[PDB]
Amino acid sequence: YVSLADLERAARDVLPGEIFDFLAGGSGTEASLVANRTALERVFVIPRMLRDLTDVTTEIDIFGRRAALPMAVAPVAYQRLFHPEGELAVARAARDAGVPYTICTLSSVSLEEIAAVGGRPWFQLFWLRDEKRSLDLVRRAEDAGCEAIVFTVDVPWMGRRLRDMRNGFALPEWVTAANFEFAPATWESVEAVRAHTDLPVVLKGILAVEDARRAVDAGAGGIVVSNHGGRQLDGAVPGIEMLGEIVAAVSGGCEVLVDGGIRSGGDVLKATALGASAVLVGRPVMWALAAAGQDGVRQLLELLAEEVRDAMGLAGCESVGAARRLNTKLGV
Amino acid sequence: YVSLADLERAARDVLPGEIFDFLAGGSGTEASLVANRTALERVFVIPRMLRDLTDVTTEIDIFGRRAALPMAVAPVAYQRLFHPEGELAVARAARDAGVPYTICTLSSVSLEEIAAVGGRPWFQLFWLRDEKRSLDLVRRAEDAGCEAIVFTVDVPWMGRRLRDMRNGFALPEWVTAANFEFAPATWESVEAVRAHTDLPVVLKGILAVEDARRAVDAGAGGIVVSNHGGRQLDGAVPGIEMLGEIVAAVSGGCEVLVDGGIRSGGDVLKATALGASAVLVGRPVMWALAAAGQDGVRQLLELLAEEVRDAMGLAGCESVGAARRLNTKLGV
Amino acid sequence: YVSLADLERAARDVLPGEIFDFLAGGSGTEASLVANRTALERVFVIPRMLRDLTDVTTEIDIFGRRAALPMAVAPVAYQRLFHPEGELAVARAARDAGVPYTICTLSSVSLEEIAAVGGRPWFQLFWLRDEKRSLDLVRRAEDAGCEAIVFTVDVPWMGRRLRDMRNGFALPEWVTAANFEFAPATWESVEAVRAHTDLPVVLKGILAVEDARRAVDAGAGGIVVSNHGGRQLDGAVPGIEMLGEIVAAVSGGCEVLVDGGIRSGGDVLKATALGASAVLVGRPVMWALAAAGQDGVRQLLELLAEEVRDAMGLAGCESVGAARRLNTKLGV
Amino acid sequence: YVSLADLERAARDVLPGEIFDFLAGGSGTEASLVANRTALERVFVIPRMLRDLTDVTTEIDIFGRRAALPMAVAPVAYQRLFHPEGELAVARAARDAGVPYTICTLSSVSLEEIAAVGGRPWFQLFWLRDEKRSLDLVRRAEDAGCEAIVFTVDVPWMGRRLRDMRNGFALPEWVTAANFEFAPATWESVEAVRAHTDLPVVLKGILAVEDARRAVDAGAGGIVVSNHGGRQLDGAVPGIEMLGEIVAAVSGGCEVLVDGGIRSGGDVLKATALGASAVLVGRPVMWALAAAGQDGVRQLLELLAEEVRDAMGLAGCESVGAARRLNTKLGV
Ligand SMILES: Cc1cc2nc3c(=O)[nH]c(=O)nc-3n(C[C@H](O)[C@H](O)[C@H](O)COP(=O)(O)O)c2cc1C
Ligand SMILES: Cc1cc2nc3c(=O)[nH]c(=O)nc-3n(C[C@H](O)[C@H](O)[C@H](O)COP(=O)(O)O)c2cc1C
Ligand SMILES: Cc1cc2nc3c(=O)[nH]c(=O)nc-3n(C[C@H](O)[C@H](O)[C@H](O)COP(=O)(O)O)c2cc1C
Ligand SMILES: Cc1cc2nc3c(=O)[nH]c(=O)nc-3n(C[C@H](O)[C@H](O)[C@H](O)COP(=O)(O)O)c2cc1C
Ligand SMILES: O=C(O)[C@@H](O)C(F)(F)F
Ligand SMILES: O=C(O)[C@@H](O)C(F)(F)F
Ligand SMILES: O=C(O)[C@@H](O)C(F)(F)F
Ligand SMILES: O=C(O)[C@@H](O)C(F)(F)F
């Protein structure tokens, strides 16, 4: 595989159409899904030349741990849909690559089993009608050694997934929510989580500048600037279009991650040049899992690491910090 | 039907080609028709997160009545072209949905019959060569319980409808103007109408900012920012491109509606975020009428209501007022 | 014929391919040719409503004569290529429509014969290696009753017409330059012409603002803002993109015409709203001549007059002056 | 051949697919490759009229020598891939046209043999792991009569060429690096070269404004504003998009060349109007070499010279200096 796009072709060959559509699809007309890609394609980097590249490093420190790349595996529900080893296959590959893996509230293997794989696991939280269940998940995650709580704030309820409605998609009987209904979360919910854990709380799905600022004021350790991969509000701005403004507004008060459409090391470099601390990658990780299980995810992460290192050095950056100081230009 | 676009396919299957073209078409090269869609597609919403959504309401108060959604059925001439029940089928579905229905001067069922259906009917006025006939229509509408007069100001004469000219389109003998020639209207005409009724006068087809201001000064209760669905001046700016500027200029002095190309609850949300009080929807209502009569219109209005509620809540808006405070970003 | 585009189809059916290509083609990659159209398509008009339209008039006064529309027939060489009656067919139709016709230096019927048709003829001048020949043409034109000299300033030599080179195009033996080598013209040439005639001198092919200003200072009575229909410099800006700036800079000091890609009454309205005094129309007139001779040109001019009147009134303009006061908005 | 695009078709017919792909391809998704073209296509020139064109000259003085056009042949590795005469065929045609030819460090004929052809040769330098080898190349180039050292600064290592990876491309046994591993170059390397030669040092692959300024401060005699034809960082801005800003920042302190996508005399004119001293042309020269050897390159250079002269005069420029004073407008 020489690009992330070779894996999409392979995943489409193997998965049942309705599962491929659950993975690929977005809400509504899929305008936000498409715009995630368009928005990245319009960003060009202004590389620097003739800098010292004797020891290029792609590592970052985030949430108190060193990561091998400025990237983590995004939360994706129900990974046994894609391969029988599901979350364990992905978590193992992420561990071996030194990349954080986000364990989902809707994981198809229990969070404690996935955490036992090792590595840098984070835990993604959905707020539930029964509040106590959400807070018990947080405590379970912490007890299992998760290192951050990624609170998803953009799903008061699931968006309108027309592919899924047209297909009549439902989980097969062999895939369940192994940790066991959505309730709208509020800033009060954020505070209840912050009070119940010593782990950094990361709010995922922030797009308004004033929500980024309020996240810092609320004691968040990070945010993920994100439109949920075009799966929630159809017509929501891409995160990459808000990122620069958000990074300026928080002025270092929390980590600022971005996601949506990251498909190469070059895209990682764009995100960092716009100011991101790190990116999340969702669909491509699942393409690799579908295509070739743990080995497939390993191969994807190896390719991404090579592309990140290549892009960084070609742009004159010996570190991710230097990459954040790059300028960009919008084009056609 | 899971989107408004499923109904277009169904209407195209059933209607005679020349009737489908009377409905779908615009003037000239159809540049303004296409631009209505392009203009909406370029607008992205910046949603807010973590707000209280315990009681999301899509209702608005407009022209002294509560409406279920920030939407009304646009005036569309000759609805018996599309289904034998014509305007009565649409008006009944609108009533049942709590949406205002605009009875047309060129209705194929008499305005008094349509008004007898009940609901929130408005009445659309064309100025006629015989002035007295226009003013008699106003009095008839008021006597029948219509709640606003929507004075169409963008049709001094009908535009050049090339599909209709190529098809040699004419009304079948079984479709007539049941209320019974266009004369250019002026500001004097507006004043003659205002003096002849106690109902709110709404000027439909305003696109220049200074015409919006003058509408307020003239005593209008509302305007509809509109290029008549691309059917009048070919090359007229889309209403959605003028809306923000217009809303700022009138600074709350009248209701500011918009139309043209509204095809989802997401589009309704864009219009409100740009400042609209409400939208009109034309062609999609007729697609539903063609496809399945009253039931079809009911299904469309149910789908739109679900999409509006979904979009609002995903954007952190418990009310339409909150949606008007959302920011937007233009994209690709 | 219900649009100018119906005539292109008809002309393409009848003309030999190499003649159609001589007519349609531009220089180089035809980037400027295509951009003439793109540039007009991006301009939207902001129409005004509720104005008096009791006596809409499309007339203008230009170069001391009343014209029926704000349009003239552009200079096009060798019109016997397109129809056996050539320039006489076009000139007769223009006369009957009350539109000025520009007689070309490279006319395939002598300028005196065309002028004898009557009407409002103008004369287009090429500067020649033998200066005296150019100045004799001017005197001949004036003696024959031409009312303006349109000095073409953008053809120091003919551009690179790749269609013509690929086709090996040459004039058939039955088409000649009936008035009988290009020399670069300079401001000195302009002055020599101005001194040799009492007619208004119009400089055709101006695109830089400072050249427009200098034209006024040089005593020009008009300019034509133009990239020669994309036939000269490939990559020259469209005239329509320079027009507003030019109109502001000359601040009424001469008439400012535009050409390139005008294909409807709506396009005429755009040009006027951008500030043009009038437009020239080239290729469409020749399509009509190819399709149906004098009658074809008459039909085209009738259609254009109807479209201009329609566009004007739909935009709230009772006169061309009012149309010049319209605002525009650039779109997608 | 009447355009540079006729030669691409001819080269694609004759070359083995993998060699055509080595030539045509870029890094990654080829976003930067495509953007080089897009960026030029959006630039329109504002031509001037009515200037003296009695003695139009396309000559420039650069690096102490007169060149026939504001263009040089870009460094392209391994030209025996394209034709058996390789670099000697191209160098001979360049000499005969009065265009500088850049001899490559990776030339498939030795630099001394190519320099013996005569003409204006420049020498392109790669910095090597063994520094002394790079500096020996510089001395060899100077001893052989090369007139400038073009130090390539954008290849700390070769980019990710996915066409080449998919094809399993490798040099055939009959093509070698005849002058005989990449090491990242730094500003220290630049200074080591500057100290080892009296020739002008030209830094090729500059895109950041501050790197342009530093190049001047470092004693460079020129820079080439360039993204290496889209072959290095995928997502690097096109040079043509940085050029104006760069030209302003150096304010005449060194020659500022540009490359990437130059495919006509019209494109040369755009580059000069944006401020370039001269352009480099890569792929088209190799298309001509593949198609017809020395004669093919001669024909290409003749066509380019004709197009440059044509564009200049149509734009009212009797000299390249005048062309640099032209204004431009971005379009669609
Ligand atoms: C199939 C699928 C399931 C997902 N499930 C979740 C989830 O349970 N929680 C969450 O916060 N995000 C979820 N996401 C969103 C991703 O975390 C991420 O925001 C999105 O996929 C990023 O875009 P990318 O897929 O373009 O890389 C899901 C995304 C996909 C494609
Ligand atoms: C077939 C048809 C007939 C119409 N008749 C009228 C009319 O009689 N009066 C009027 O004010 N608008 C009329 N309109 C315009 C609509 O009220 C509305 O401005 C336009 O359809 C809105 O755009 P939409 O169809 O894209 O939703 C008509 C539109 C269509 C498509
Ligand atoms: C076939 C052809 C021949 C032309 N000959 C002349 C000419 O002799 N003199 C001149 O000033 N313009 C000439 N023009 C340019 C036109 O006057 C005009 O600038 C151009 O056609 C306007 O664009 P349009 O064809 O898009 O309407 C010619 C154009 C065409 C298409
Ligand atoms: C096949 C190929 C090989 C190249 N080899 C070199 C090289 O050895 N050194 C270098 O500085 N540039 C090299 N370049 C880049 C060119 O010098 C130039 O920057 C690029 O081709 C310019 O773009 P153009 O090909 O679009 O005209 C190469 C380009 C191509 C296409
Ligand atoms: O995007 C998803 O599918 C998840 O976030 C879910 F299942 F929660 F909506
Ligand atoms: O758009 C329409 O068809 C109506 O507004 C009419 F019939 F009046 F022009
Ligand atoms: O555009 C044209 O063909 C004319 O202007 C000519 F023939 F002069 F170049
Ligand atoms: O672009 C190229 O192929 C050259 O610059 C090389 F071979 F050095 F990378």
Image (cartoon, coloured by chain):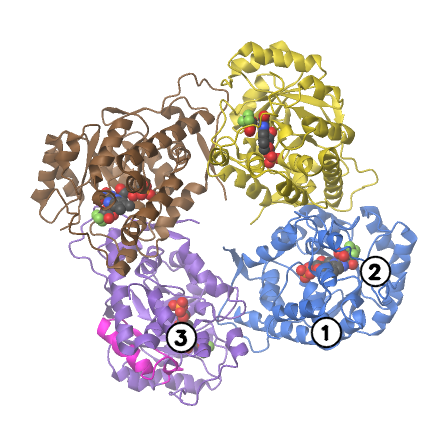
Chain colours: A blue, B yellow, C brown, D purple
Judge: label 1 CB < 8 Å from ligand 1: no
Q: Spatial distance from mark 3 to mark 1, Cα to Cα? A: 38 Å
| Of the pair A132 and D243, the residue shown nearer to us | A132
| Identity of the residue drawn at 48% across and 31% down | B233
Residue that numbered label 1 is attached to: A98
In this view, B210 is above or below C220: above
Residue wearing tag 3: D151
Residue drawn at point x = 83 percent, y = 66 percent: A146
Look at the numbered disc 2 and say if its residue's Cβ is closer than 8 Å to ligand 1.
Answer: yes
Residue of label 2:
A105
Residue D99 lies in the magenta-colored region: yes
Mark toward the viewer: 3 or 1: 1
Residue A324 in the figure: left or right of residue B156: right
Secondary structure beneath label 2: loop
Q: Is residue A247 magenta?
A: no
In this rendering, position of residue C75 left or right of residue A323: left
Tag in front: 3 or 2: 2
